C-alpha cells in the first residue's frame, strides 16, 4: 500500500533549514498553493521519508495558518534510519507525501491557564500550543523548556526574544544530570482549572508525573515520542508466518514487520510508527518477540506484538493475521 493509496497528500518542501545542532526545520506547502487541511495545536502528521519509512512529526506553526505545515526533525544517528533519511536525502523543492493531520494532543477547552513543559525536541507540540494560546489571546501560559545548551536548543533565538521571554523559561543542564531544574516550586500549588502538558524524554515525564501526584485528576497530560531507541548491537533478519493468511515473509535487518506487511498489502492499522499509539497491536501465536514498544505491559508481552517497532528473539514468529 503506497502513501497515495493510503490517502497521503503530495506536498512540496518549500524550505529546509538547520535550526540547532542536529535539528532541521521543514516548511511544507501544497505545490499549487492550495490551502491545506486544518489542524489545531498538538496535532501530528505522518511523512513518507525518502527510504520508504513513515515517520510522525508534530506541527509547530500557528494553527490559524492555512498555507503551510512546519515540522522540526532531530537527526537520530542511533535511530532506525528514518530521521537520517529525511534529513540527509531531501532537498528544498522536493515532493514529499504527508498524511492528514491527526488531532491527538489538544489543548483543553475549559482550562483557564497552562503550564507547558518541553524537553529537547519535545518542544514541537508545546510550541504549537504556545502559538495558539497567543493567537487566541485569552488564557495565560508558562513554558518551561529544558535542553542541554543553547546550540542544541531549537527555536532558541525566537523564544529568547522580547516577544517571548516573559512566558518561557529555558534551563540548560549542560550534560550534567546533577544540574537539575526545580520542578517542585513549579508544581507545589495547583491553581484551579490549571492544566499541565508535558512532552520530553521519559525521565522528564516521570519527574513531572511524580511532582503532580497531588494535582486534580485529569489536569496533567503527556505525549511520548517513543521508546529510547533500543537497537541492541545489531538488528537481525527473522521470518514471520501469518496464521490465517497462510503466507510467510522474511523481515530483513533494516525493515520493520509493518513495512514488510504493508508491501504485501496486509492491512494493519498504524499511525505513530513509534510504538506509542497502540494501533498496530497484533496477536503473536508463537515465538519470542523482542518488544521495543511503550503500550504493552509485561502481562501481554507473550501473546501480543506492536509490529511497527518490535522484532524477534526467536528465529520465527507466527502472527494471527
Ligand atoms: C506523536 C509523535 C510526535 C513526534 N514528533 C516528533 C517531532 O516533532 N520531531 C522529531 O524529531 N521526532 C518526533 N517524533 C519521533 C519520530 O516519529 C521518530 O520516531 C524519530 O524521528 C526517530 O526515527 P528514526 O528512528 O527513524 O531515526 C514523534 C513521534 C511521535 C510518536
Ligand atoms: S503504529 Fe503506533 S504503536 Fe505501532
Image: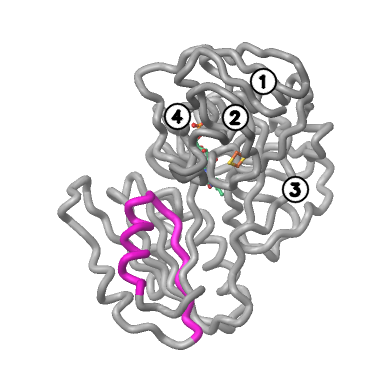
Lower sequence index among marks 4 and 1 = 4
In the rendered image, the quadrant that contains the N terminus is top right
95 left or right of 113 in image? right
Question: On the image, which quarter does residue 82 sit in?
Answer: top right
How busy is the neighbourhood of tag 1: few (under 14 within 10 Å), some, or many (20 plus)?
A: some
Q: Contact (CB < 8 A) between labels 1 and 2?
A: no
Which label lies toward us, 1 or 3? 1
Q: Residue at x 62, y 39 (%)?
A: 281
Task: Pick the residue in front: 150 or 282.
Answer: 282
Measure the C-alpha gap from mark 1 to mark 3.
Answer: 23 Å
For residue 143, what is the image quadrant? Answer: bottom left
Look at mark 3 in the image and give the residue it sits on. 100
- Residue lying at the far left of the rendered structure: 178
Chain part drawn in magenta: 193-213
Residue 4 horizontal/vertical position (percent): 81, 32
The mark lying in front, picked from 4 and 1, is 1
Q: CA distance from mark 3 to mark 2?
A: 31 Å
Is residue 311 visible in this depiction of the protein?
A: yes
Residue at mark 1 to residue at mark 2: CA–CA distance: 17 Å
Vertical order, 154 against 302 (above or below): below
Q: Is mark 4 within 8 Å of ligand 1?
A: yes
Q: Residue at x 78, y 27 (%)?
A: 2
Instruction: Give percent across and percent down for residue 44.
Output: 63, 51
Q: Point out the tag, 1 or 3, that comes first from the N-terminus.
A: 3
Check contact, mark 1 vs mark 3: CB within 8 A: no
| Residue located beneath label 1 in the image | 260
Residue located beneath label 2 in the image: 284
In the figure, is residue 207 to the left or right of 59?
left
Amino acid at each position: 500500500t503506497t502513501p497515495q493509496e493510503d490517502g497521503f497528500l503530495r506536498l512540496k518542501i518549500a524550505s529546509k533549514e538547520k535550526i540547532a545542532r542536529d535539528i532541521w526545520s521543514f516548511e511544507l506547502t501544497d505545490p499549487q498553493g492550495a490551502p491545506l487541511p486544518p489542524f489545531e495545536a498538538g496535532a501530528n502528521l505522518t511523512v513518507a521519508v525518502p527510504n520508504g519509512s513513515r515517520r510522525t512529526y508534530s506541527l509547530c506553526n500557528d494553527s490559524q495558518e492555512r498555507n503551510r505545515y512546519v515540522i522540526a526533525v532531530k537527526r537520530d544517528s542511533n535511530g532506525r534510519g528514518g530521521s537520517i533519511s529525511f534529513i540527509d536525502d531531501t532537498s528544498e523543492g522536493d515532493a514529499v507525501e504527508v498524511s492528514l493531520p491527526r488531532n491527538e494532543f489538544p489543548l483543553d477547552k475549559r482550562a483557564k491557564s497552562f503550564i507547558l513543559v518541553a524537553g529537547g525536541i519535545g518542544i514541537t507540540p508545546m510550541l504549537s500550543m504556545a502559538r495558539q494560546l497567543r493567537a487566541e489571546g485569552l488564557r495565560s501560559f508558562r513554558l518551561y523548556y529544558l535542553t542541554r545548551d543553547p546550540e542544541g536548543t531549537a527555536f532558541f533565538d525566537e523564544l529568547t526574544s522580547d516577544e517571548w521571554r516573559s512566558d518561557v523559561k529555558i534551563h540548560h543542564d549542560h550534560g550534567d544530570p546533577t544540574k537539575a531544574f526545580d520542578f517542585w516550586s513549579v508544581f507545589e500549588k495547583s491553581k484551579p482549572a490549571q492544566h499541565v502538558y508535558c512532552c520530553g524524554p521519559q525521565a522528564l515525564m516521570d519527574t513531572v508525573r511524580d511532582m503532580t501526584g497531588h494535582w486534580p485528576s485529569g489536569t496533567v497530560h503527556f505525549e511520548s515520542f517513543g521508546a529510547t531507541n533500543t537497537n541492541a548491537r545489531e538488528n537481525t533478519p527473522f521470518t514471520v508466518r501469518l496464521s490465517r493468511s497462510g503466507t510467510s515473509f522474511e523481515i530483513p535487518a533494516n525493515r520493520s514487520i509493518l513495512e514488510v506487511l504493508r508491501d504485501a498489502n496486509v492491512r494493519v492499522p498504524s499511525s505513530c510508527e513509534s510504538g506509542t499509539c497502540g494501533s498496530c497491536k497484533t496477536a503473536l501465536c508463537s515465538g519470542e518477540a523482542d518488544h521495543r514498544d511503550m503500550v504493552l505491559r509485561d502481562d501481554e508481552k507473550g501473546t501480543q506484538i506492536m509490529v511497527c517497532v518490535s522484532r524477534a528473539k526467536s528465529a520465527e514468529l507466527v502472527l494471527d493475521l
